[PDB]
Image (tube, rainbow over all chains, first blue to last red; front, side):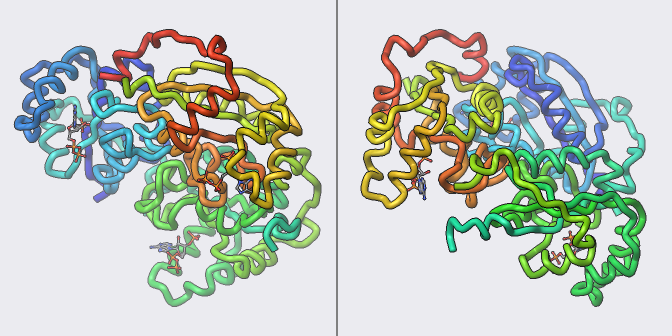
Length: 151
Length: 157
Length: 152
Ligand SMILES: Nc1ncnc2c1ncn2[C@@H]1O[C@H](COP(=O)(O)OP(=O)(O)O)[C@@H](OP(=O)(O)O)[C@H]1O
Ligand SMILES: Nc1ncnc2c1ncn2[C@@H]1O[C@H](COP(=O)(O)OP(=O)(O)O)[C@@H](OP(=O)(O)O)[C@H]1O
Ligand SMILES: Nc1ncnc2c1ncn2[C@@H]1O[C@H](COP(=O)(O)OP(=O)(O)O)[C@@H](OP(=O)(O)O)[C@H]1O
């Protein structure tokens, strides 16, 4: 419910093109609560486990190499239906189909340079959060606006 | 008729709810209507009485959320507004996004700024008939200001 | 290559009058499209009649030409993968009544006849429009510093 969490990663192209603050602002202004935030170079072992559902796809090795080629911003956000709603805010996975107003619709063009990843399901979010963050890196606090965001 | 000056003079009632005020979204919301080309006619900051809210939401008096909605709308100040323009009722609703924020698209006010249906930041008239009733209920005629936008000939044919 | 497709975008006199030039350009730059041509001009009625030749028999044609000649326009050429189709998506529906929030027309204008901008509808129309509005020498070629982060 209101405490659902999702994993969002800003990809190396999102960092290189100076979109970190823009992306974070979209989640903050929506009313989602920041739980975790890290900046790192993800190892190929970590990326292969993150993208384990894609291990049989032809683009898998290139996606892992690319995701390891620069730093990423790993994040955890909390809120009601944050997994599904986070995916709507990102826009379609393929930027060609993403609508203006979405992060990919506004800021990127091609699927291998799509700036961001968001968990596709509550099950995938729980696995991704556990893989990228130690439990002690996730911060719990109450937003001063909680009563104005949720009944 | 299409292209008539009178069609450009349609008005709608928009209220920024207590959560929109609390979360500092008043300026953001007003900027969206101004940049679109809609003309501001009325604007006031007020605490709406429960009697005014019960009449505003009279069609919902039998819904289970009615009492909570009236209490919530009375719990803080609201920004009441009247905007004018071609199809401003329907287009204002499109700009707000779906009533339930879960279904509102990015780019819309609710799509960008809020999450749950009971805390949806804003109300807009659902039809020209509801707009006429709502404008009359929230504003005295002397609070509605008429003027001509300097960009009128660049917004309308 | 497919990443070198080009489209023609014109900001109409109402877009210039209402101070939307920078906002429109920012939308194309932030998307990752490359600016190729940019010129500010009063389009002649002869140029506009050729640009809108397919509408010469429509009842609104004379008013459209007069309107497009009534003030300056910003003529532009942008480059990128599927920039024609994607540029149209970014502009929003031709009729602003049907354009969604988040698009240029959805955010900034209301009526057809004052719809702030034009974008090529097809690669064939883009080639014709670019040739009509720009001399080849006005089109600038350079490589974006972010090319490898926009395209694989
Ligand atoms: N050709 C490709 N090159 C690189 N990554 C790709 C390619 N096709 C798909 N993907 C990635 O493969 C993942 C799955 O995308 P799909 O389109 O197959 O499914 P999805 O729309 O349900 O996410 C996406 O990763 P992301 O969530 O980190 O964006 C997508 O970007
Ligand atoms: N659970 C709820 N709690 C509070 N208000 C609600 C709830 N469900 C619906 N409403 C409100 O009830 C009003 C009518 O919304 P509906 O979606 O029911 O519309 P409808 O009656 O045509 O279906 C909306 O008010 P607004 O225009 O000021 O936003 C909507 O927000
Ligand atoms: N009543 C009208 N007055 C002025 N221009 C019009 C009118 N109806 C259509 N047009 C213009 O006629 C052109 C063709 O619009 P259509 O709706 O017929 O087709 P489109 O949606 O497939 O592009 C558009 O020009 P633009 O690309 O420069 O915007 C459109 O604006």
